[PDB]
Image (cartoon, coloured by chain):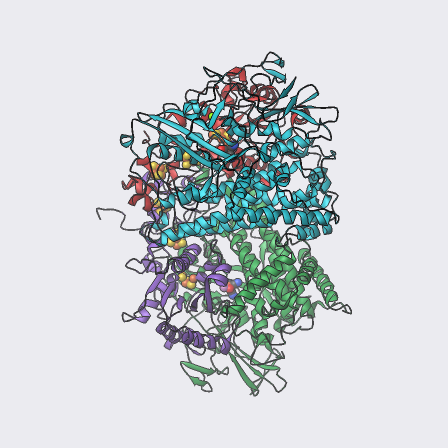
Chain colours: A green, B cyan, C purple, D red
Amino acid sequence: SVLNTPNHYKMDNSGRRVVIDPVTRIEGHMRCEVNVDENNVIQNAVSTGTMWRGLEVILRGRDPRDAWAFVERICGVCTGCHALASVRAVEDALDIKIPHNATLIREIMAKTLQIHDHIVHFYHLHALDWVNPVNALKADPQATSELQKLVSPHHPMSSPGYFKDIQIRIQKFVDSGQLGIFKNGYWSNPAYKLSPEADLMAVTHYLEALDFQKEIVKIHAIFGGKNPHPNYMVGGVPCAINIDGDMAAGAPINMERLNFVKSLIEQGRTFNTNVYVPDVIAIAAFYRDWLYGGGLSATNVMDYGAYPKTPYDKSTDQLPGGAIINGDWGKIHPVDPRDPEQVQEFVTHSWYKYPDETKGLHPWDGITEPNYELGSKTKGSRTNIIEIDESAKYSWIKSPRWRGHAVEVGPLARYILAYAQGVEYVKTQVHTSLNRFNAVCRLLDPNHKDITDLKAFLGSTIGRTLARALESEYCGDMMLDDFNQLISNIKNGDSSTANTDKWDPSSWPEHAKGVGTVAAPRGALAHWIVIEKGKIKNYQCVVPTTWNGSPRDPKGNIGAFEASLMGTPMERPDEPVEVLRTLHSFDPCLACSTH
Amino acid sequence: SVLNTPNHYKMDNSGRRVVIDPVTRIEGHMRCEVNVDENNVIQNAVSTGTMWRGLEVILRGRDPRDAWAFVERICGVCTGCHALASVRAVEDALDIKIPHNATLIREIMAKTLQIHDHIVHFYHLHALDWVNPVNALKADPQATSELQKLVSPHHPMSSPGYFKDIQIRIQKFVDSGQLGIFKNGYWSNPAYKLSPEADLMAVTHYLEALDFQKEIVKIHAIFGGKNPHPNYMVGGVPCAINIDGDMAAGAPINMERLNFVKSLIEQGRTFNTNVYVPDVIAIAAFYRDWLYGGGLSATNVMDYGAYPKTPYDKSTDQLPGGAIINGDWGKIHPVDPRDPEQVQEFVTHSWYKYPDETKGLHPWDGITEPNYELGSKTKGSRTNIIEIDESAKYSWIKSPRWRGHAVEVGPLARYILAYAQGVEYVKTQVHTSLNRFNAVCRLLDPNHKDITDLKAFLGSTIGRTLARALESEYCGDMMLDDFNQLISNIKNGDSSTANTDKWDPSSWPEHAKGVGTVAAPRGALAHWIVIEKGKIKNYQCVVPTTWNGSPRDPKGNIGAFEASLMGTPMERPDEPVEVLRTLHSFDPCLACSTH
Amino acid sequence: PRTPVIWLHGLECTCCSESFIRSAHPLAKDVVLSMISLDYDDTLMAASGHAAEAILDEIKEKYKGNYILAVEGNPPLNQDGMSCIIGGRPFSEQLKRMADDAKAIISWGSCASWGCVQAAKPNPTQATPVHKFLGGGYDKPIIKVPGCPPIAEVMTGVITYMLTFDRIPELDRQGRPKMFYSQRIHDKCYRRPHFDAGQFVEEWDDEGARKGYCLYKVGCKGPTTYNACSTVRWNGGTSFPIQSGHGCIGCSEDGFWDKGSFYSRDTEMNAFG
Amino acid sequence: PRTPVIWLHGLECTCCSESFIRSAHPLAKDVVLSMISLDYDDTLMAASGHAAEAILDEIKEKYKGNYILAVEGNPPLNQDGMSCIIGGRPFSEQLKRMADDAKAIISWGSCASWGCVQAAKPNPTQATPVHKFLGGGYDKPIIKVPGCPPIAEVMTGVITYMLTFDRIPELDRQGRPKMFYSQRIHDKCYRRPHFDAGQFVEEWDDEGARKGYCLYKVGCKGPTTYNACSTVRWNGGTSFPIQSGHGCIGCSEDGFWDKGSFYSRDT
Ligand code: SF4
Ligand code: SF4
Ligand code: FCO
Ligand code: FCO
Ligand code: SF3
Ligand code: SF3
Ligand code: F3S
Ligand code: F3S
Ligand SMILES: [Mg+2]
Ligand SMILES: [Mg+2]
Ligand code: 3NI
Ligand code: 3NI
Ligand SMILES: [O]
């Protein structure tokens, strides 16, 4: 068939079918199928979420104050963001305002998660789509050192002997014949474009990042007890503050704990600036001729907006939200998660049932009733899918749309929205990153002509990857501001952390509904709760990967993952490096997507 | 006067007198006075310990089981070594044999101390006698990187941008006009011979060492609760072991704690070999024409011997002891701390009283009775000493002698003794270090003639400084061996840590005496205890700096400090860089020396 | 040769995998490069799709009876198992095939050990912990390392114990290593002096909260929870839930999600009950 | 301009100075470069003798009434004070001279706070803690930070508090910051459940020792000792005496050396 989608794609499944199941180096479980034409160009893409747990069903009848802990376990990668959305949703329903220090500490925890999640994503999940560790074994350590000094002059770890020592270790690993995570990698695929020296630099930084990442989450351990899965509460934060009073040493937050947080923040800022951002820029330069994967980012992007400089005042959001539609960056459409005509979820191509499946349901009206059922054109059987039938139900992911539009969410969406709304910090990051990208390109190709087209640059797999790294850096700077504000509040006499006026259900209205939003690491997250007589009547999550990984809607619009693959040539369709590189650039979280 | 000492020095106090009080960058309090001739060459040297606390007096009548904690507080720099000597002395007196794991854990704690103490000494106490931080501000960062790569190819921290950033920080500090510890440093003195690049490299490593040193002592925190001042006990170690049994997580030593110790050991080994040892070798090469300060080291050296591969079998000491006398390295005289004709302390030039002050007292017969009294040739008064009278009593340090000989103790003494006794590990370190030294010399001077004379090389302030660094590296290797043995013991079924058979004083002899020896960071340490009816009758300490910092004896022999200064030319007698450099090379611990 | 480890993922949130890489000692980098051979792990592995499934087949045959099978998450039995699909087939089939030839199983976390959040009422996928799925006839050890997630150094501590001492650690009746799970939180809790004195947080951010008083009245499940949180603690010994001011929610105990509200008070506190 | 700090050393073992540089956060390098101006400290100074003495004179004049005087160790009164000689004169004279013009004093450690080991019976040097030496008429704050030594992060925590919040921390009746010294070890001890159940180490390396049972019966002085050891803990939160299996010896409490054997029960 050839399907002409309302969002201007031609989905053609007549070509050779390629199946990727499991998609690895993601959180959770995904299957992807594509069709390629005679020139090995993708002409159809099918996103299948291959897990479901039913948190929305499990929550029914429980106490809203307990919800945050259940939904936190939607995901251990984006650990905490669901807890944050939950407490915000309950607080919204019950008209609870939290103390300023609770606001600040929650944002510090959120920005800690952003940095940790972005770093580990790029190195531990994404890098092996750009980096060939076997090729690193061919590098000259002195030339690797020279490249390192150009890539990031401030990073101290550049000795040729250090790179040689890393190389010896990877050589020993390879020589053992136990290749572990590297086994069966597509290392001979010409899709890998780094020099041996760049591969060795990147492998070195994968190891440095694995060492570093365990440090930054100590901020979650201080404020939230543990990472993964720090604690939250409705009405405040549990980490009471006592700097100077009786038994301060035994309080959750005292002078020593604050000094520890300061040290951790600065370490994160340094890693962002000296390792992560320069690597993404330099790797992007090596791949300067590979600008595929833009998909919907060119046209339709959305975020709810986050990080208000003034608590509870969205006009001060440091990552302002809204929706850009049809590529018009000059028109920011306001997004209201309360409006039943805006966020809606369809299930016509998902493994769920609605009484009326023509309907898109706003999440206060959402329904989660499983319906695992394969289309009659499926190749295989109910417990053995060979080729999924995308004309019918093909995913555990629902199809969210915004006023009927399919949109992309994530750091790139936020960066577009912030750039378009004149956020100077972001505009400066974008322009300096483009200048740096062009500089490294010229190091590699002395005849390089500068890229100037911001839509082409940002609206790509490379751009999506870059935006994530830039967002990490921005979060580190914002977190330091938050910390300084926390110290100022304490200095000005405010050590308060919780509001308990509405802790007891006797204080609640008989019927209430609320929505909590979060700029989660992968994009726009919200939870919608309906409370009745002290209990959860409905609880519906629409999460970033739900948006990006969405199957088709009743009109045939394709979601962000499927769009991003369309038109991409593959060197070797059966060694699908390009598909993985682009899918991974969305940082898919499949447990999130399905919950 | 001109005094012709039996140990072949001519102490002449007719020339200009220079007084250094306080001697800074040591532990505790010292005064040093010298006389210089018309050529600015030192022709007299006077070592004065300027503190006393009286631990030996304080211990009288107390319980031998409590002694370790009192004497540990003799010193917070060599923290632990006195506790170790004490428990060994009590165990010796009472014929207590400890379990193998207790032996091993004590040796791991000892080697931890050696590494910490040696590193912090070199960088934070000694380096400013060799390193000019002001001159560092003139370094080229690229050339500093090149030097770093040659000095220690494996050390990762070599980026020009890193050295530039360090320089910027030091420049900011200097520009503030608050010079702190650098204020009034002798920075224009030509005695400073490093290039600006070597100064910058060294300052950078001073900072790296300050960050590192807090890590290695976590081994003391694990086995001993805390550092400074970890806990010990008579009969074993309190850190009971439970790897696999009920409540293991709550035992002092469990699987996670052992994994922590492994990590810490390896970090120390890395710092020894990549930072500390290479720096001392390279700095030595810049100072290749400054071979003063040997003093007694080439003639008379002593250590009790330590670190037996087989517990309680001294023939297996990895740093074997003995005494070399009159420069005959081919004759190792056995040292017995029990022999009243061997170790003796005189007080004729010390602020103490004996009934018969002609006598040298073996420490089981030792007496500590203060007698602060100044010679009638003193310039000044009892409470305002302008020039001390070294013809009379001039120090709180007693005068220990070995069979009437003045000896040098410390890492250099141990290194000479080990080399002379064919310890292959040490011989390899010495030969490789000399080769490396000569290689760096040849780079600074292509016409360099290799040094081959081991007595001249080792028997100098440079050699004394090098031996300390080599010993640190040896201790890291030994400590790993100890850790592996501990694991093996546990694996073979032995988790025991204490012998309690003689814990109760009802099990002790009415009268008992013992001696405990330690290869302390600064040299030969021993404690001698006499027990009567369950109480301390006498407790006498003779500490490494007691030996080295000793005032003259009745026959007029000078001690190691005084000997080391004799014959040294000074660029500027009133800016006594050379005196500080040589004194500091002994790592004076003045609280130790006097106790 | 380094010990082969196959790390499978069922229905899960991936928190145990995340916790593992937080390990302060040994570092995860050293575990993977030098201690074990992490032969399959859909989270970190270079290969996908057919290339990934080829490894499972190869390791199963080459190292038959000699690999450790680590399992995070759990198999669903509803939806014909297709609420967790891997390679087009139910995860339960992958789990069974690999369990057949494992030397031993490590059930990482509360999902694999007990069921965790997806198993809470009404358990729409019939998520089933590994030991119950394989049944009473399964003849290899199943080492349960529960917690949501477990402590990082507990996870790596189990592995280092097996590699260093050449045996499975002693397990309690529930299959948990005594190494780490043989005391209750409340048996080693630094806030116990306050519990003893009846000094409690009564309301969030009250006087007691700011003094670090006991969290029993705000729902601490430490009295009934066996784990190393109050001894080893979390994130390189930085903190644990109680230190940072929220009661234990019981996250390593079988059935903790349905035990009661997290803010309900813990039971069986009196000896005269 | 960074806050001027003069750090004097009397009779001491230098453990407090060592502890200070163990600080995990802030790092000692950052304290000295960026937070305070450590203007005199015999342990670390480049200059010696006359050049070192010249600094005390200079700082005392330039920053009269504006420097913090940190004191480690204590002054002896016996031997005419010459059991601790600095620059040819009794340390007590240096201490008095600098105290006269200090903004405030920090008594680091049990030596400066109380006397510590040299003051234990029979106190041969008549070592005297700073507050007693200066007497009741002394009109500037004396902040006692006791312990042998104090915890590293307690020491740097006191400094960061003063720099961040612009006041002396609240002190208890003994002059100790409530920040750190307002609970007993036993009031926050993770072995307390065992104490409560009568589960004790009875002999070294017995079953109880291997289970981490309470150390009361082997002499733990936790029940009477105010410090942060069971909360902040030692060496970047790595351990504390009790965790590693030895009872508290009471090392932050006035007179702890003469309270009795460390292995005798707390009464
Ligand atoms: S109830 Fe919780 S907070 Fe209180 S002592 Fe027990 S485990 Fe600690
Ligand atoms: S006596 Fe000591 S070990 Fe026992 S609970 Fe009290 S402080 Fe802890
Ligand atoms: N970020 C993140 Fe996870 C997803 N998708 C959530 O919410
Ligand atoms: N090392 C050391 Fe201290 C001295 N001298 C002791 O003993
Ligand atoms: Fe660590 S996968 Fe996270 S939900 Fe509770 S253990 Fe499961
Ligand atoms: Fe830290 S100098 Fe060490 S003895 Fe007890 S505090 Fe004094
Ligand atoms: S909630 Fe879990 S992490 Fe520990 S403190 Fe309680 S078992
Ligand atoms: S001995 Fe001292 S270090 Fe703390 S545990 Fe007791 S006060
Ligand atoms: Mg949903
Ligand atoms: Mg003595
Ligand atoms: Ni997620
Ligand atoms: Ni000492
Ligand atoms: O996620």
Q: Is residue A273 above or below residue B210?
A: below
- The image quarter containing residue A572 is bottom right
Residue C43 appears in the figure: yes
- Give the x, y percent position of residue B389: 61, 17
- Give the x, y percent position of residue A118: 57, 61
- Give the x, y percent position of residue D103: 60, 26
Could you say which is closer to the camera, residue B57 or residue A181? B57
Q: In which quadrant is the N terminus of chain B drawn?
A: top right
Q: How many marks?
A: 0
Instruction: Specify the farthest residue to the left.
Output: C272
Relative to residue A171, is residue D198 drawn left or right? left
- Give the x, y percent position of residue B570: 71, 30
Could you say which is closer to the camera, residue D28 or residue B156? B156
Instruction: Specify the farthest residue to the top.
Output: B376
- Which residue shows up at 58% across the image and 53% down it? A268
Could you say which is closer to the camera, residue A581 or residue D266? D266
Q: Is residue B197 above or below residue D74?
A: below
Could you say which is closer to the camera, residue A593 or residue A305? A593
Q: Is residue B105 above or below residue A37?
A: above
Residue B123 appears in the figure: no
- Which residue shows up at 75% across the image and 48% down it? B447
Relative to residue A161, is residue C249 drawn left or right? left
Q: Is residue C124 above or below residue B531?
A: below
- The image quarter containing residue B420 is top right
